[PDB]
Amino acid sequence: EDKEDEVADLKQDTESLQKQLEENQEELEIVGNMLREEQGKVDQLQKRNVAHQKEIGKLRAELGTAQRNLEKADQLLKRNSQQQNQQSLDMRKLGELEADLKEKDSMVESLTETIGILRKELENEKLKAAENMDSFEKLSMENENLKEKIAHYRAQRF
Amino acid sequence: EDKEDEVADLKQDTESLQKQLEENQEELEIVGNMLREEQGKVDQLQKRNVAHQKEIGKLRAELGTAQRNLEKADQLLKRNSQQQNQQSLDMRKLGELEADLKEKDSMVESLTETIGILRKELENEKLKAAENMDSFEKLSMENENLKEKIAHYRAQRF
């Protein structure tokens, strides 16, 4: 209480405490924004995150249908044992047939060769037959001349 | 009476102020945390997204091949099928052969018919020519016999 006591020390000091206030209010704005945007990002990332939830969804159906379908149409390629087994069943039935028929064809060829001979031996014995019965007539003829000549002797013939 | 009630007034001006810088730092305390907590949420979502996106590329290839396979094994169903074209022609045209067997079958049975007959007719032409050989010998034996009777008669000239 003597002329001057704590003059501006109180006056120019509230400005201190007042200016610090000037900041915490500014900065609180800066952080206020960053927050608005960082939570802004999460809006966009959170979205994309399901856009992928979807894309990845589809693929679980497609790689499934296509992997079990490779089995669905693979049982049909398992019939390659019934289809190639016939290469044993059929190559034999056709293989043995081309052999047992080509052969039975030589028979008919060997047989008709003999039917050809029997047709000839029975051809000649048809000739030697007529031919021999011929030598008989000449003899049958001469036979008579003799019966006569002898008949005359038993009587006539001076 | 005023120098005493002066610094008393600046107090209030500082009471109200010190409160603000305090109550305010509480807003800045929280709001600062809210921000970081979001940046936490962001950075990470930024990850699962790169996780999915990368792993969406894997399923993309697993689907790719798994499809080429469904087709690579399907060309093979076009070949397994066309062998049904040649296997059918083999099961139907092989039958013509087992059928062309009965043609030669009836032939070798039909020829042994004509071979059996000629062999039997050859036997009769032989039985016949066996008589003629006999009735001829009788004859020859008769003339030979007569010439002799005759030659005895000729014994009347001497």
Image (cartoon, coloured by chain):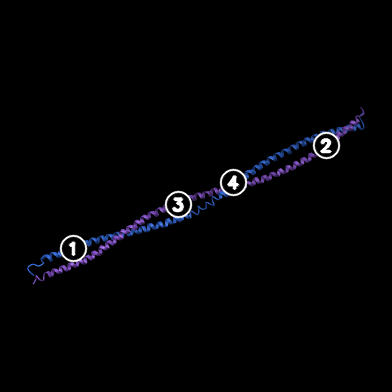
Chain colours: A blue, B purple
Residue at the extreme left of the image, as rendered: A3
Badge 1 crowding class, 10 Å Cα cut-off, few under 14, some 14 to 19, many 20 or more, is: some
Instruction: Specify the amino acid type for callout 4.
Output: Gly
Q: In this view, does A45 lie to the left or right of A90?
A: left
Badge 3 crowding class, 10 Å Cα cut-off, few under 14, some 14 to 19, many 20 or more, is: some
Residue shown at 12% from the left, 69% from the top: B7
Instruction: Report if the CB atoms under discs 4 and 3 are less than 8 Å apart.
Output: no
Residue shown at 14% from the left, 69% from the top: B11
Q: Where is residue B62 in the image (x, y as percent from the top left)?
A: 41, 53
- Mark 1 / mark 4, whichever is N-terminal: 1
Instruction: Report if the CB atoms under discs 1 and 4 are less than 8 Å apart.
Output: no
Instruction: Specify the amino acid type for callout 2.
Output: Glu
Using the numbered discs, state the Cα–Cα distance from disc 1 to disc 4 in whole angstroms.
Answer: 109 Å
Check disc 1 and report the residue beneath it.
A20
Instruction: Specify the amino acid type for callout 1.
Output: Gln
Check disc 2 and report the residue beneath it.
B137
Q: In this view, does A22 lie to the left or right of B53?
A: left
Using the numbered discs, state the Cα–Cα distance from disc 3 to disc 2 in whole angstroms.
Answer: 101 Å
Question: Where is B3 relative to A31, above or below?
Answer: below
Discs 2 and 1 carry the same chain letter: no
Question: Mark 2 against mark 1, which lies toward the viewer?
Answer: 1
Question: Mark 1 against mark 4, which lies toward the viewer?
Answer: 1
Q: Is mark 1 on a helix, strand or loop?
A: helix
Discs 3 and 2 carry the same chain letter: yes
Quadrant, the C terminus of chain A: top right
Q: Is mark 2 on a helix, strand or loop?
A: helix
Using the numbered discs, state the Cα–Cα distance from disc 4 to disc 3 in whole angstroms.
Answer: 37 Å
Check disc 4 and report the residue beneath it.
A95
Check disc 3 and report the residue beneath it.
B69
Tally the numbered discs.
4
